[PDB]
Amino acid sequence: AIGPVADLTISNGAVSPDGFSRQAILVNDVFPSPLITGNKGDRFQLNVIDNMTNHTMLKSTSIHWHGFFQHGTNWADGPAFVNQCPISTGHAFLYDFQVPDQAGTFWYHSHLSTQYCDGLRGPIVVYDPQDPHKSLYDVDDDSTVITLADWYHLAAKVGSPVPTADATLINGLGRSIDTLNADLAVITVTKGKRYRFRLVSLSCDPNHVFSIDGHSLTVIEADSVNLKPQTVDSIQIFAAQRYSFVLNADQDVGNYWIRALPNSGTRNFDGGVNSAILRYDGAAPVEPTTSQTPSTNPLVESALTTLEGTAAPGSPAPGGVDLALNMAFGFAGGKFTINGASFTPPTVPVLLQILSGAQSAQDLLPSGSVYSLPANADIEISLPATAAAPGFPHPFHLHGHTFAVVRSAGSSTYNYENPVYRDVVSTGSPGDNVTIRFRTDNPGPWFLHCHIDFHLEAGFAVVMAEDIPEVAATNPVPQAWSDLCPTYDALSPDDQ
Ligand SMILES: *[C@@H]1O[C@H](CO)[C@@H](O[C@@H]2O[C@H](CO)[C@@H](O[C@@H]3O[C@H](CO[C@H]4O[C@H](CO)[C@@H](O)[C@H](O)[C@@H]4O)[C@@H](O)[C@H](O)[C@@H]3O)[C@H](O)[C@H]2NC(C)=O)[C@H](O)[C@H]1NC(C)=O
Ligand SMILES: *[C@@H]1O[C@H](CO)[C@@H](O[C@@H]2O[C@H](CO)[C@@H](O)[C@H](O)[C@H]2NC(C)=O)[C@H](O)[C@H]1NC(C)=O
Ligand SMILES: Cc1ccc(C(=O)O)cc1
Ligand SMILES: [Ca+2]
Ligand SMILES: [Ca+2]
Ligand SMILES: [Ca+2]
Ligand SMILES: [Cu+2]
Ligand SMILES: [Cu+2]
Ligand SMILES: [Cu+2]
Ligand SMILES: [Cu+2]
Image (cartoon, rainbow, N blue to C red):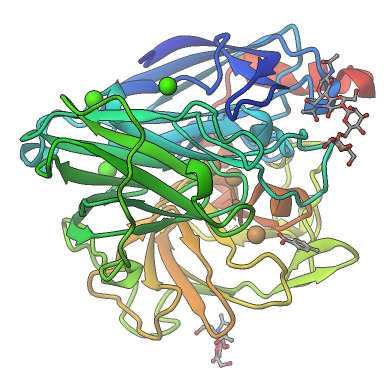
């Protein structure tokens, strides 16, 4: 892997991850984007050098480091027009931040429009030298990162506004229905060894039901949060989520199908679509002939708990917090709404608005989309599922924070004692009332949005303006950040 100090050069080029070729986005001349790693406590210095020339996929860029708290470095978080203006082509920008108090599985992706769908997205691992789960496994390295991704034959701005994927990629490879002989990813294991696999969803839209024929999976991490171990036989993973699971390679030496069934597009495994190969050392170099058995032990989010058994912030009753917010989803004029407002990117990034003197949510643009949060407070947010926002279940993501999921999708119970904490949560289907809690210990504007990128583009977002009075003092910005907007605003539209 590369990192924690590295150049990330962004360019355009042709790729063929499902045996069909198209123009896309390369990072350090490769697709899919390379793995970046560090250790707990490391300073990351990622110099993003933008050499893109294709306006259809956008020449500008901005990168989000998904899951990092960015305390004191809100300017480095990535969302275009929230935390920065985009980097302009022919320029570079250094993201310089620390990860003092976090370890686990993360990822990076463009956070400008729908650009990450065109290929700028890759995994990150922050290792913990004192990982409490470390004695459960033998192997945890580049080879044990498993990414899932949707792939489209037409680019994000070329196809339908809400497209359906032609292929699922596993570690960057997969088959489409018209490319049944395309290359497949192979993950190799040695019989008798134990592996920490780190499963990362780079998806722009679909969720995937992940399973491995003949094997159970011991889940030990969700979205960079250590869990009490939970053995499962399938995992439904939503866009932008991560899980670590331990696999004991104790079955017969052979080839076993790795499966990732999407919730849209091709919903079968015919011809080896939506599949990869688990190969034991010594097995024949052939495709598996294993069968899928019904999942009788699927992952259930409400049954997950943190390793430390951390209580939810606040008191154990509905509304037992300093500020309770309800987000009512809707859809009007082809745009998503939250509490009647659709997010449209402001000309001046929200952070720059605050640093320039905006004092309240009413002062902040876009109007109706920004919520001021008090400092050092317990917050509860409910996000009740509704068919009024098409394309459910919507996996919501809160920047700058992990949150307690006090009520999960598909469950009527509330857990304040020992709920799972994570950073992306499915808000489920009608009848659900997914409810989250967090503490406001991190001054800055933080995006809260559906991580289905096509829905974000259609306005399905709000901004949480946390502790506005302390933002400037807590987040001193580098000169290079100050220069982003004047450079970007000087571009002609066709160079954006
Ligand atoms: C930079 O970025 C872009 C995005 O990657 C590039 O866009 C490509 O540009 C061309 C047009 O110049 C496309 O080819 C066209 O595709 C359409 C649609 O094809 C599909 O749909 C039709 C109708 O349903 C169907 O008949 C076909 O079988 C396809 O399924 C065609 O109608 C056109 O005739 C033409 O073939 C590309 O599809 C497109 N690729 C990306 C992935 O969307 C662009 O080329 C880049 N510019 C630099 C110079 O390379
Ligand atoms: C889901 O969650 C919230 C919070 O429990 C609900 O909104 C609250 O519900 C009651 C009754 O209407 C009120 O006492 C409060 O004023 C509400 N608090 C929030 C901050 O507005 C809501 O009713 C639920 N929605 C789904 C449909 O069950
Ligand atoms: C309007 C509309 C329709 C469908 C979707 C979707 O994601 O399926 C999103 C928006
Ligand atoms: Ca091969
Ligand atoms: Ca291996
Ligand atoms: Ca962690
Ligand atoms: Cu993300
Ligand atoms: Cu994020
Ligand atoms: Cu959505
Ligand atoms: Cu985001």
